[PDB]
Amino acid sequence: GSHMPVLITRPLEDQLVMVGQRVEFECEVSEEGAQVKWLKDGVELTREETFKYRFKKDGQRHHLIINEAMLEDAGHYALCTSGGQALAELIVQEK
Image 1 (cartoon, rainbow, N blue to C red):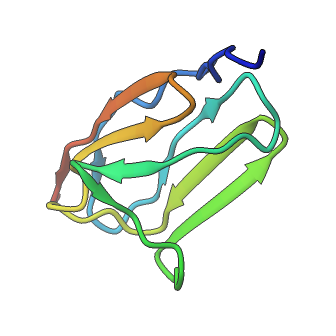
Image 2 (image 1 turned 45 degrees about the horizontal axis):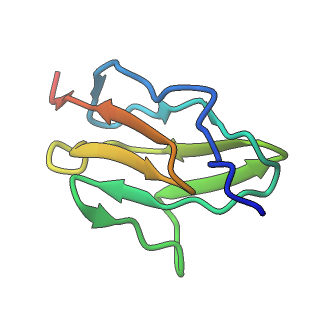
């Protein structure tokens, strides 16, 4: 039956940002409107009330735009899908 894994066709950003600067990540999956899961170093990001983080779904692509990245907020980002794995390591520094 349906056993094809939703693959993340676009790997996560590998690059470091600064405090007060925005972070743009690009990620796409093999299915539009596909189910995903955003984890920051193991901690799931809450989207029940978001003023800092914006989660946008445009077809198969997903964008998490961080308005202001913090030091401990960089963590290790991991998009958990139907079984496609992308990994992002973010380093935020106060410049």
